[PDB]
Image (cartoon, rainbow, N blue to C red; front, top):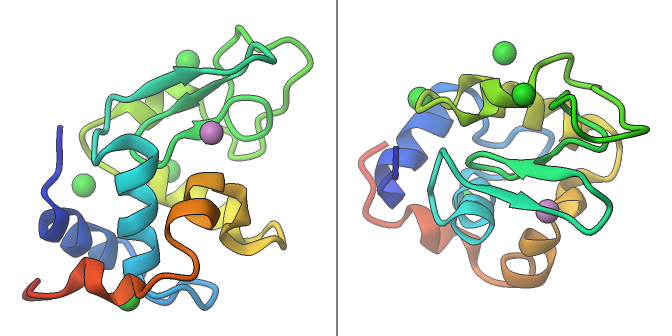
Length: 129
Ligand SMILES: [Cl-]
Ligand SMILES: [Cl-]
Ligand SMILES: [Cl-]
Ligand SMILES: [Cl-]
Ligand SMILES: [Co+2]
């Protein structure tokens, strides 16, 4: 699925991200835009042999098992394939674990580089949530 901005905003709200660990919904929408371009199927290979998966580009070195990342962990206890569903539940649930790992949304460099410091509330403007 390729989500629309407000479509994703609504789905993330329904799955409990609005103000999760102190991060307003706009942060999550902005992160998804710059990580995956709202694309649930997005994958990107990394220099270390890990891959980023799905709408929030969750990395196989720490968070999910793809059986092709030597030395990696699976801290969300899920196969990375689950993060390539059109339904965002698995990605949201794993993101909640990532953000609670005690470094906030800094885990998403695209968020820190392209969202943090901007008015992220603009990302949910005009959505009827
Ligand atoms: Cl997998
Ligand atoms: Cl969904
Ligand atoms: Cl899940
Ligand atoms: Cl917001
Ligand atoms: Co990445």
